[PDB]
Structures are given as structure tokens and as C-alpha cells.
């Protein structure tokens, strides 16, 4: 597709609150959180560690509902 997802731009430790440096946009398979939502993710905490290059999925972010 042309649908991009949010992909971790650095290792994000468990329980870190997301900042814009941590999130890039990439076309990856499977599809994760839409790249369009990166503004809406700042300050939300991840509930597990996300290695560099991992697609951010809905279940990894605390409080995320879309």
C-alpha cells in the first residue's frame, strides 16, 4: 500500500512517554498505528520495550484508542 505506520526511530524503553524524536513514518507490513497519528501519541506511554525499527501497534500504547 501507500499506507505508512509509526515505526520506532530509537529503542523506546518500557514505560517511556513518547516524544517526536522516537517516531518515524514508514510503509511496513503488518500495518501498525497510522503515521497520521504521530501528533496524538506524544506524551503517551508504551507498555513494553519497543526496539529500534519496530512498528508501533495499538496494544503497545497505554490509553491509545483510535
Image (tube, grey):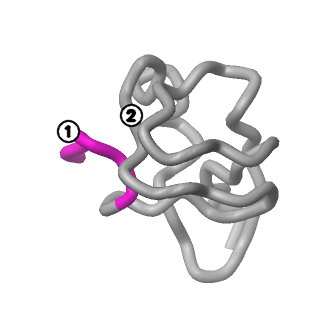
Left or right: 16 as drawn, with respect to 53: left
Question: Which quadrant, please, contains the N terminus?
Answer: bottom right
Taking 20 as reference, is 63 above or below it? below
In what element is the residue under mark 1?
loop
Taking 29 as reference, is 47 above or below it? above
User: Most prominent secondary structure in the magenta stretch?
Assistant: loop
Q: Nearer the viewer, residue 37 or 20?
A: 20
Q: Position of residue 56 (x, y in %)?
A: 54, 57
Q: Nearer the viewer, residue 36 or 45?
A: 45
Q: Label for residue 50?
A: none
Q: Position of residue 51 (x, y in %)?
A: 72, 59
- Residue under pointer 2: 45
Q: Earlier in the sequence, mark 2 or mark 1?
A: 2
Q: Nearer the viewer, residue 32 or 54?
A: 54
What stretch of residues is rendered in magenta? 60-66
Give the distance between the C-alpha atoms of the residues marked 2 and 1, in whole angstroms. Answer: 8 Å
Instruction: Kindly indicate whether the residue at mark 1 contacts the one at mark 2 (C-beta within 8 angstroms).
Output: yes
Q: Quadrant of residue 60?
A: bottom left
- Residue under pointer 1: 63
Residue ID at (35%, 58%): 58
In magenta stretch: residue 52: no
- How many numbered discs sit on the rendered protein? 2
Q: Residue furthest front?
A: 14
Amino acid at each position: 500500500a501507500n499506507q505508512a505506520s509509526v515505526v520506532a526511530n530509537q529503542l523506546i524503553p518500557i514505560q517511556t512517554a513518547l516524544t517526536l524524536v522516537m517516531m518515524r513514518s514508514e510503509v511496513v507490513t503488518p500495518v501498525g498505528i497510522p503515521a497520521e497519528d504521530i501528533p496524538r501519541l506524544v506524551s503517551m506511554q508504551v507498555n513494553r520495550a519497543v526496539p529500534l525499527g519496530t512498528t508501533l501497534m495499538p496494544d503497545m500504547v497505554k490509553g491509545y484508542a483510535a
